[PDB]
View (cartoon, protein in one colour):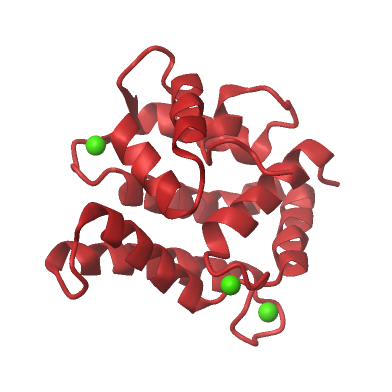
Length: 183
Ligand SMILES: [Ca+2]
Ligand SMILES: [Ca+2]
Ligand SMILES: [Ca+2]
């Protein structure tokens, strides 16, 4: 129902971008930590105005994730619960659209700290470094996304997002939106 190419991409997002604390299970505290880690690299003090926008944005991703995938209502999203959602969307892709669109927008919002509506290499790399990825490797992943440009527009980002979550092609540029892939 889900190709190994897409499984690899789904579990990379789960293990790197959702499970910040590496417990193996996704919980609200992972997204509080994610906001803390990004704010620390940006030099945004906790309780600062900029910090609370970032934390709110991160809590909004968590609640959308919890509503979609926490099937047993324990307040946690297992790796099996994440893959189980995507088996559901494989039968009814049309139902994925509202949530995917909100998640796409949230992820772009967290990266675009200048609010100019494009993601530059320092915006992209800084967020990747906060999630524990290699700087040089994220710099290379950015170069594969930006097609020669200094910035990724919102419009380019929505296309790259669709490829990352939908394409069974192991080598489309959208496969780089969450940096160099983990196996
Ligand atoms: Ca966790
Ligand atoms: Ca659960
Ligand atoms: Ca920007």
